[PDB]
Amino acid sequence: MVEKGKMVKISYDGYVDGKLFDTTNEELAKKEGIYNPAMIYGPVAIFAGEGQVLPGLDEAILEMDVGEEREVVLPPEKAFGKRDPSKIKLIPLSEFTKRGIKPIKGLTITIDGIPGKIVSINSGRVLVDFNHELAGKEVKYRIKIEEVVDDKKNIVKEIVKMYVPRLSDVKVTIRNGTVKIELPEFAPFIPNIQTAKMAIANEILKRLEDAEKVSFVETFERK
Amino acid sequence: MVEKGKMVKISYDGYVDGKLFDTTNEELAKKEGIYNPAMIYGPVAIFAGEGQVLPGLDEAILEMDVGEEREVVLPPEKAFGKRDPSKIKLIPLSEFTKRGIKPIKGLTITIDGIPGKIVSINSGRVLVDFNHELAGKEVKYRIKIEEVVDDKKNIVKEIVKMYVPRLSDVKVTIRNGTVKIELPEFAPFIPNIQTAKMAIANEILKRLEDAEKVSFVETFERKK
């Protein structure tokens, strides 16, 4: 069993109706058609049982051990939630034609700034589902606990990556109460890096009781 | 003389037709009415002869010594430019009325943002002068070279202040071609501080040719 609040690194592959919809395995993601060039793959760090993942995943993780691999089946209540009937709405077909849109099943459209999926067309009404795509669905996860991170240096490294995935190679130095974090050359250019830094620092101070301060170093070279 | 590229701190008072329009002196800006709460006054650092001041003013500085003070009368070509006759145009009066504007002679208005002074109104036509306000005017400066900033540490500090006036108190250390700048507690919250930091680093690396890197240190304390 893994204790609530423990930082763990996990790998997983998430299936719905036989199909892979999410994974930390880059190669598999490629093989299976869902690869996102913006996403950073590989094992992910979470604080166990704190709500960083699906509730059913949090529950499964807390009863596993390090090195343990496992497959869990989660009901919608524990995954992406039940399908709310209030979010499935009949919209007059004229609302589409007037805008020059041919409604087709599976088309994503937006109404009032809210996205929905076209579910069916009958007579002069288009049924559009504004629920989460995986709402009401049972989902399966391959999950493995890769490691427990219990050293200060790596807790900090992982907290940084948790808040900013692209920052996977930061240099951390613990010096009696001071957490020094040297950032890569590209870091200063990250959108709202400053908010991110403050969040990272706040997370570090919460986890490392002996830390008095968190100091970030940004370096600009002759490039 | 001062060499081009040298950092100097200067103090000055600028005059048009005998009236003060620009200054580094806090009190003299208020007493004369030209004060602006968003401006940090006092000696300001420039790089000599690089166009951070009016051209007539740069060229004076290049021929001055540290501590020297002099009056410099600048012709329009070296100040805000010469009056350009092609910028004084006849505009149909209907252009004003369409915009809800009442045109009065001598009274500055804006047309589509761009401001202008109404010279006259005649037979459904408005003659508007769109020259810079101080165009064609001779301006007179009282300028003193307060100090030359010659030492690496103060060059860095002044560069910081040049880009972000509020960062007047930073800790600087230089070791093995690395310039380290430790920032105060409020630094990370400054608007567009990331762009300011790259700007400061660029300037530092330009001025200190022995520098290989510029490092900024931001520190978050245990609510303190």
Image (tube, coloured by chain):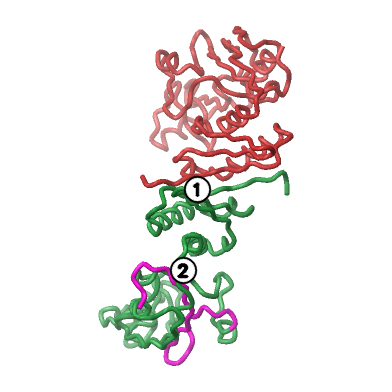
Chain colours: A red, B green
> Eyeballing the image, is A218 above or below B56?
above
> Eyeballing the image, is B153 above or below A107?
below
* Contact check, label 2 and label 1, Cβ < 8 Å: no
Outermost residue, front direction?
B176
Q: Position of residue A211 (x, y in %)?
A: 70, 37
Which of the 4 quarters of the picture holds residue A68? top right
Which of the 4 quarters of the picture holds residue B70? bottom left
Q: Nearer the viewer, mark 2 or mark 1?
A: 2
Would you say residue A196 sits in the magenta stretch? Answer: no
Tell me the tag on residue A217: none
Taking the spot 60% from the left edge, 82% from the top edge, the residue there is B27
Q: Chain of mark 2?
A: B
Q: Secondary structure at mark 2?
A: loop
Please tell me how crowded label 2 is: few (under 14), some (14-19), or many (20+) other residues with Cα within 10 Å: some
In-image side of B92 versus A148 (left or right): left
Tell me the tag on residue B149: 2
The three-letter amino acid code for the residue at tag 1 is Ser
Q: Position of residue B149 (x, y in %)?
A: 46, 68
Res B131 seen here:
no
Taking the spot 42% from the left edge, 91% from the top edge, the residue there is B17
State which region is magenta: B1-27
Q: Give the camera-side residue of B149 and A207.
A: B149
The three-letter amino acid code for the residue at tag 2 is Val
The numbered mark, 2 or 1, whose residue comes first in the sequence reads 2
Q: Position of residue A196 (x, y in %)?
A: 58, 40
Q: Secondary structure at mark 1?
A: strand
In-image side of A215 versus A32 (left or right): right
Q: Position of residue A150 (x, y in %)?
A: 66, 23
Res B38 seen here:
yes
Q: Are marks 2 and 1 on the same chain?
A: yes
Which residue lies under the disc numbered 1? B215
